[PDB]
Image (spheres, rainbow, N blue to C red):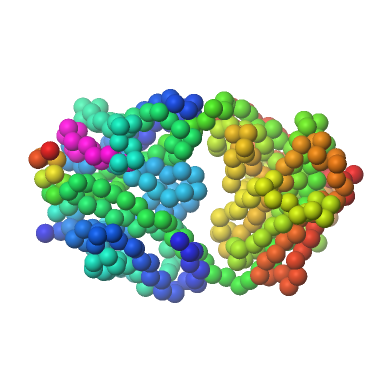
């Protein structure tokens, strides 16, 4: 379900892959914003729900159904879901969500590395954190290195929702290992790759 | 106005059962089909079942057939779901929804988080993320259960540049989270930076200063 | 007739007959 990037006032057309022509015209579209309940926009393929602007519209026949946003207002940016339903027997099947996001000028991440606190090492775990601040587009690759050894499977990633102000993303990667393994190595680095970086950026520290 | 109010968040061990309520107000509760919809964190929506206005007719999604039960009591205007044999897969926010206008989902409850895990309630540990143009610093909110956790800086004095990342579930079964803030580098010796983390489920509140 | 009342009518027919 590929994410859509577009500026305000652009057109978007979401498609729903029906099975057995759905039934009659029983397809609906829901919009959800982070931290919020979904809101119905279209049902019955084409009739709008109460309070939904005319800029939303639905259409289609057979297996092909479509939600068109003729021009995106700032409040239209959200995740959109297709709902196929029927009456005999009743059934209601959400499709995968499609995020619609604000397109923006490219912005390179600012990278920071944080060595584990002496507080945490007292407890026997060592968490190294790599911060990527205010970047667009969302696609970014963090690559931990420990004594020139590429790492995999010992880190977890987290990404903020697009910022209300500058429409940028931020990412945090936490490399976690035991205090014993942490002291067997000297150099810790996270290498960042992004569309805004002409060359990969490496932030690093030597333990102690 | 139609209003659906669900019961509060629940914590369950695997294999246990859970029963969420949904109290309706502002309408007769005798006209509308009701639905239960769930959403795992970071995932899509998933329909579970439907109940006819009398409550004598139901139709669950096939995945939950034999383990879910939905009921309705008009005199109390309450809608119920009962999920059993809970697994970690069942961790989700559960929504009740009324179909009074279309027969679909026209009005929603606020939702109820149900966390199925063998882990027990646990307040966060908090560790500084020390700063080395602009500087960065933060707090590592680690090994807490369950969600959610709220974080603030200087008890609301700081907002610009703050980022509080979504929690990630560790292999231990406890959640971990980081909150960061960008500041001018000159202020590292002239301003006190204190993260405030409140874990409501454990009623734990911790403050942590972040020196260089 | 409008789509909202019609689908609820079909749902009424399924549950009345099962």
Q: Is residue A168 left or right of residue B77?
A: right
Q: Is A120 rendered above or below residue A55?
A: above
- Determine the image quadrant of residue C6: bottom left
Residue B157 visible at all: no
Q: Is B211 rendered above or below residue B118?
A: below
- Determine the image quadrant of residue B150: top right
Q: Position of residue A169 (x, y in %)?
A: 61, 59
Residue B51 falls inside the magenta stretch = yes
Residue at the spot 65% in from the left edge and 55% down from the top edge: A171
Closer to us: A82 or A107: A82
Q: Position of residue B196 (x, y in %)?
A: 67, 38
Q: Position of residue A154 (x, y in %)?
A: 69, 45
Closer to us: A147 or C8: A147
Residue A207 visible at all: yes
Closer to us: A98 or B6: A98
Residue at the spot 59% in from the left edge and 46% down from the top edge: B166
Residue B86 falls inside the magenta stretch = no
Residue at the spot 72% in from the left edge and 57% down from the top edge: A143
Quarter of the figure with the C terminus of chain A: top right
Q: Write the start and end of the magenta stretch as one range.
A: B48-60
Q: Is A15 rendered above or below residue B207?
A: below
């Amino acid at each position: 379900p590929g994410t859509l990037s577009l500026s305000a006032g652009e057109r978007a057309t979401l498609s729903c892959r029906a099975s057995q022509t759905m039934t009659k015209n029983y397809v609906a579209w829901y919009q959800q914003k982070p931290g919020q309940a979904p809101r119905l926009l279209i049902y019955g393929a084409s009739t709008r729900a109460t309070g939904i602007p005319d800029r939303f519209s639905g259409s289609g026949s057979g297996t092909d159904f479509t939600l068109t946003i003729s021009r995106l207002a700032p409040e239209d940016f959200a995740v959109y879901y297709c709902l196929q339903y029927g009456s005999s027997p009743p059934i209601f099947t959400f499709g995968p969500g499609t995020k619609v996001e604000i397109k923006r000028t490219v912005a390179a991440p600012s990278v920071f590395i944080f060595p584990p606190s002496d507080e945490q090492l007292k407890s026997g775990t060592a968490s190294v954190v790599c911060l990527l601040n205010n970047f667009y587009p969302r696609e970014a690759k963090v690559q931990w290195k420990v004594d020139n050894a590429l790492q995999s499977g010992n880190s977890q990633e987290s990404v903020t929702e697009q910022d209300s102000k500058d429409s940028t993303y931020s990412l945090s990667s936490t490399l976690t290992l035991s205090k014993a393994d942490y002291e067997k190595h000297k150099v810790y680095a996270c290498e960042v790759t992004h569309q805004g970086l002409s060359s990969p950026v490496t932030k690093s520290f030597n333990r102690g | 106005q139609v209003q659906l109010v669900q019961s509060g968040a629940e914590m369950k061990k695997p294999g246990a059962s859970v029963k969420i309520s949904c109290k309706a107000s502002g309408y007769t509760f005798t006209s509308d089909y009701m639905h239960w919809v769930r959403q795992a964190p970071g995932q899509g929506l998933e329909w579970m079942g439907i109940v006819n206005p009398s409550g004598s007719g139901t139709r669950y999604a096939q995945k939950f057939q034999g383990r879910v039960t939905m009921t309705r009591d008009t005199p109390t205007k309450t809608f119920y779901i009962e999920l059993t044999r809970l697994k970690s897969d069942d961790t989700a926010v559960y929504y009740c929804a009324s179909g009074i206008l279309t027969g679909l989902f026209d009005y929603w409850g606020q939702g109820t988080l149900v966390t199925v895990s063998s882990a027990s309630t646990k307040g966060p540990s908090v560790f500084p993320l020390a700063p080395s143009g602009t500087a960065a610093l933060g707090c590592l909110v680690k090994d807490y259960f369950p969600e959610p956790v709220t974080v603030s800086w200087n008890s609301g004095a700081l907002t610009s540049g703050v980022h509080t990342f979504p929690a990630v579930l560790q292999s231990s079964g406890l959640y971990s989270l980081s909150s960061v803030v960008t500041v001018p580098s000159s202020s590292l010796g002239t301003q006190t930076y204190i993260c405030n983390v409140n874990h409501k489920p454990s009623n734990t509140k911790v403050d942590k200063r972040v020196e260089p | 007739n409008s789509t909202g009342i019609d689908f609820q009518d079909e749902l009424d027919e399924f549950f009345k007959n099962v």
